Image 1 (cartoon, rainbow over the protein chains, first blue to last red):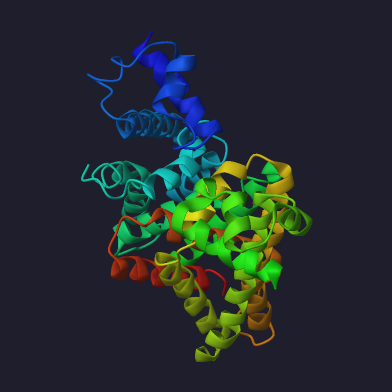
Image 2: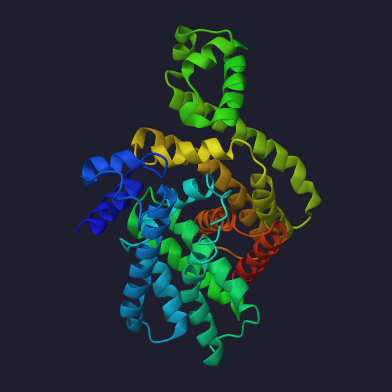
Length: 185
Length: 186
């Protein structure tokens, strides 16, 4: 494919290098195409990016729903999601690029995705926490808040520890999950 | 002092133009030093930059030392510290140069290694709070080192990935996290 040949390079480059690091040109080189390509479906550079964030985010959320079955209680689903977050090949491997990007385009008026993609990012925690209320596993009045806090705290543990033994990572994340859930009841 | 003049001039350049755009040439001339002297003190731009970060870290700790008096109990020092981490970065000028740098060197072990010794300094703050909290029955934590890494990285996640909301909400959420976390320790 071609449109899905560029994305494959954009993704790989945004991961290896940074957002700025890789530019419209660099893509075309390895992606092997021209300028026009990036016009109809691929408007601006930030467009080709927000696109990938959409894909990747969906791939992850999909993989989660296919694997969330191994977790019988929502308390287990919480633990699992956070753990899985450390090993997926999806979405999380772009957080560094997201930061860079967000701090270099939070000017344009299209912080619309960053607040549209955010809902999908914290939705898994929304469902997990909401369902937990239906199962009496816990009682949280401010779900939306907790969801946001959890998603970001976790994203932090995954992103700012990406420089050490992965079993150490998985250990921490679990001690985290424990402490969090424990502070909820 | 010529070393200090470089660190100072370089800090501003990085702040005004970012890491990548800033060159050792500019730094050399504006600090009225030389390529040779710059090499002898820091060898590289990356190293020069890590030194800046080191100075800053030191200043942050010095600021904390003073600021933490407003918090009598460790429980409070926890709430306060996390709040400071979020509010101060909201307007930290070097922040942009750190990002550019960090997300461009998290692939080299040489640099990523020194950046860990650096964050460790940041994490020590939590380590102290928790240990002192133990020796006061504010809580009981057998895995202080662990909790400290967790607190620090979770707080950082809230600070970094929340940027898309008004500051009072951010503060509110942070304070909410500090509550949940502190509650899950008793």
